[PDB]
Length: 145
Length: 146
Image (cartoon, each protein chain N blue to C red):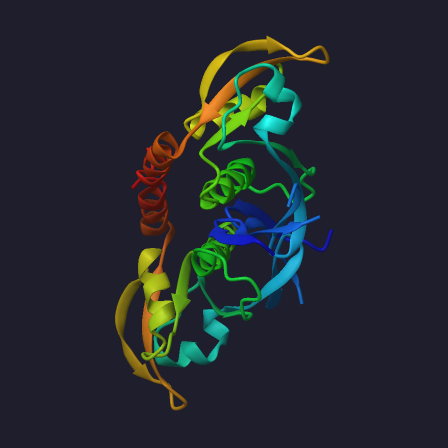
């Protein structure tokens, strides 16, 4: 197990299925995360991918036990992990423009949306996050407004 | 089906089912606490004050934390109180904590319990303390703010 932290729902951890990580709450698996370097992935074809650019895909299993704010706790765990690695300079994501739930999460974490791209299988938004705006969003979250 | 009460909290879905005088408490279908639930008039406590019609008390025991979860005691405690106040026969909650049990006193106070006086019950020195809906509801408003 690579990483752990505490949230309201319980203790979140990450263990390798490094490029595909299983995520658990209280030792129960509840999400999959794919973790890639931007340079070597499809997304690297649509912009000038830099050294330090990493992306992620995230899948959250359906909720038998429906727990408030669970998506935000997963998402923020994932980002906190990526930013715990000093080689990760910037997080790049390519959410499908229709996937409204992931855009809410992205924006809450300080992601900046650049422009849409057509990747053939989907139209995506290209969006970035660095530590500065992420840490500021964490401060927003702790101020409870 | 055997569930008498359920409510949602940050840690998950909380439920109560019979083990009604002994109830088991679960979070996301995992048992995590025992509550004994008695009418004050008929209990050892009734011998130390003028127990009224409407007076109910209880005892709460919380299992060891396999996974420690933020604010869990308060979510359990508060579920227990919300449950007691969901019963229209319960006019007043009466508690008799040991004067040394500092953890339960924080919980009681945070839910708007008013401490009356100490009582030597033989096996312990306890505080007698009451809660009615008015001050509990106000404590719930406090929690929902910050």
